[PDB]
Length: 195
Ligand SMILES: [Mn+2]
Ligand SMILES: [Mn+2]
Ligand SMILES: [Mn+2]
Image 1 (cartoon, protein in one colour):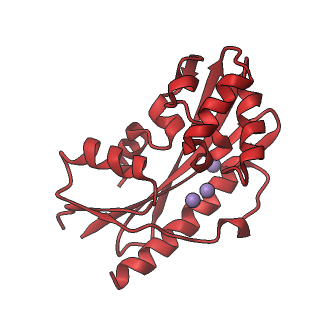
Image 2: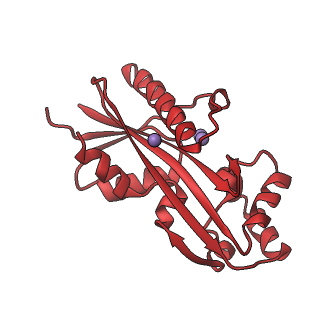
Image 3: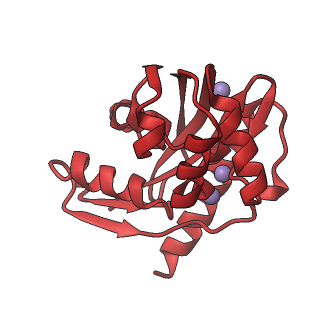
């Protein structure tokens, strides 16, 4: 059995881009197949168990979709933790504004679960990835500039470290910026090694 195909089981353009770039030396074929599930149905308090339940639910949906259009499938789920609050994608500009403003002069975590499955098998491997990003102080003006670009709406906690203004206020990251953005290749490399 020679596996040459990766099923990219996410709608994230960034994730798809990194996967093709980093894993094109191993895989010939990259198939886009987003899970498109109702994530609101899953509600665990622990963000590690939360993201894991969602990544596994996403994998189930992807493998089902694969049956009707040898391979490995990958899914992901990621949330932000700020203080005691678990944050997903913001529901409005107002909440996003609030989210971004709160990152000034402090630390913010991301918690994720990556899942991997060889299509046709029953074992779904999972791995967690956690980051912590530390910002210097910034004011309402920088908040509005980031908001105006709109990409923040599509990230957990409205956290966009790649944003022109946000980037200028990052002091350090424990982890990698690719991890904060939702796809650290080292995590996928570790899961592949566990086959
Ligand atoms: Mn765990
Ligand atoms: Mn999610
Ligand atoms: Mn999603």
